[PDB]
Amino acid sequence: TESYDVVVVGGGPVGLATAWQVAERGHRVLVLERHTFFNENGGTSGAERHWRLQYTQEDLFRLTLETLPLWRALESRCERRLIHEIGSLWFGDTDVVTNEGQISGTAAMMDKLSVRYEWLKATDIERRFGFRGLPRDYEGFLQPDGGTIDVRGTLAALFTLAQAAGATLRAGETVTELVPDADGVSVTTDRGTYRAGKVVLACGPYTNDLLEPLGARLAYSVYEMAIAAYRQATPVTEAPFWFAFQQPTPQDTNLFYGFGHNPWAPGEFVRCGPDFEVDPLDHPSAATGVADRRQMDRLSGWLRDHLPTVDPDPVRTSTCLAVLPTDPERQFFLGTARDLMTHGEKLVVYGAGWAFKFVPLFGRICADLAVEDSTAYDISRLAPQSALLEHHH
Ligand SMILES: *Cc1cc2c(cc1C)nc1c(=O)[nH]c(=O)nc-1n2C[C@H](O)[C@H](O)[C@H](O)COP(=O)(O)OP(=O)(O)OC[C@H]1O[C@@H](n2cnc3c(N)ncnc32)[C@H](O)[C@@H]1O
Ligand SMILES: O=C(O)c1ccccn1
Image (cartoon, rainbow, N blue to C red; front, side, top):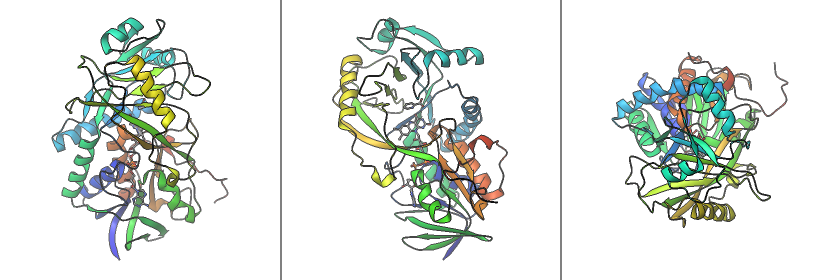
């Protein structure tokens, strides 16, 4: 049985950012990853992630401002720009309300916060970005500071930095049980056992599997989302992240999005996806890894009709898992299990969120909680929410 100050369950971006932060502070840390480092079977897949500036939630705006300098610090340390401003384009029916929000209302928020943006007509959208056949009444805005994040460069950066700082990184090892006590946490995996001062759970949608035997369960939902890669057919001037807000159809939400071009790449492929209604999974093992045929046909058919700058026959389709608070008024679960179980303060938990954009900050916070029980950042609104009735002392 090996001893560590911190054992991180999960080797995705959050786990690696946490390990790096803990190791650089001089503590003994072990990262246990069930599959391989850089795997694409969890919530982290593909080459890119979006980081918009426009929000109607004050929380997200604040998280964005606090994370920016941490990305700059990471970019400096790994000698790689990871965030690229390519723009964030929201267009279509400006009043339809969707899980992504509403254009008009978000535009009003930007007005209030002095967030700059250009308002565009259907004609402007087609001319500048190559969309075609759009209803003449579609409008939207382009927020020019919207960015796209280099996913693989970020993971390489975190892995190498954590390793250089002394973290022990182990793959192909599944944590099966955690038992916290007053002096630390006993960790069992399919390969051995370990003792930890504290454990950080950054295991994607699997958090509840390890909390269940301890009498805890968080209120988050897991969704298997479809994603397709397409070949760029025509070179273009501008290629921002885009989201098409449309009125729903009897069969689906009729919402689609594209991540935009990847500046660090040869510019050969881009990824797009449907933002359709999907029923949560009962357990992540229910995920199939097979993109839903109808959704892919709908997405490809829409690109064929409205974005001829790409070959609408996908080169590859796959899935990615989203883990989000079940209650839409909550966006992230990040704190300890202190209010959920005895000795819960010894389990630091990152349990839900649409958060690649906040990886540097969440890693720092998890590190703070694991090494000091407190963080300078206010995480009161990120409290992990229980899915069970509150009966504990
Ligand atoms: C799926 C998805 C997510 C997403 C997105 C689009 C899609 C289709 N677009 C985003 C965007 O534009 N901007 C943004 O900020 N976020 C966006 N997201 C969300 C983002 O991808 C996720 O928030 C992020 O990937 C989460 O990272 P995290 O590190 O928390 O989790 P993960 O990569 O799933 O990794 C968890 C690791 O844990 C391992 N694991 C699981 N169970 C165990 C056990 N028992 N033992 C050991 N290891 C375990 C997994 O294998 C995984 O590697
Ligand atoms: O607004 C976002 O962050 C978003 C929405 C849909 C797909 C990817 N990213």
